[PDB]
Structure formats: structure tokens, C-alpha cells
Image (cartoon, rainbow, N blue to C red; front, side):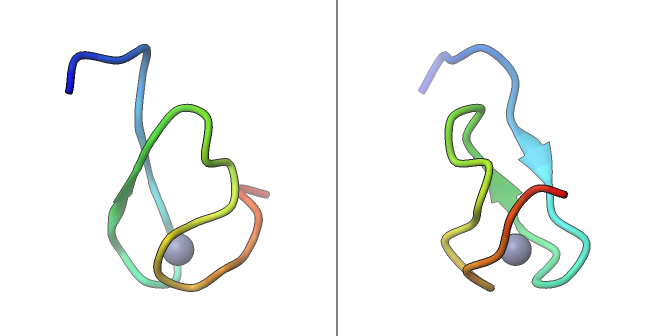
Length: 31
Ligand SMILES: [Zn+2]
């Protein structure tokens, strides 16, 4: 809801918040 810049994971293939470097799908890091 209006944030900095989300990201697209390369495991679960879902969108994630700019602060959730991990993930709400796989449970892994952004890197
Ligand atoms: Zn993920």
C-alpha cells in the first residue's frame, strides 16, 4: 500500500515488500 519499492522473488515467484528482504512464501533471503 504505497511503499518504497517491492521485489519479485525467484523461488516462490511472488511480490514482496521493500522491508521484507526475506519472503512471505519461501522464507528465504532476497539474496
Ligand atoms: Zn520467496
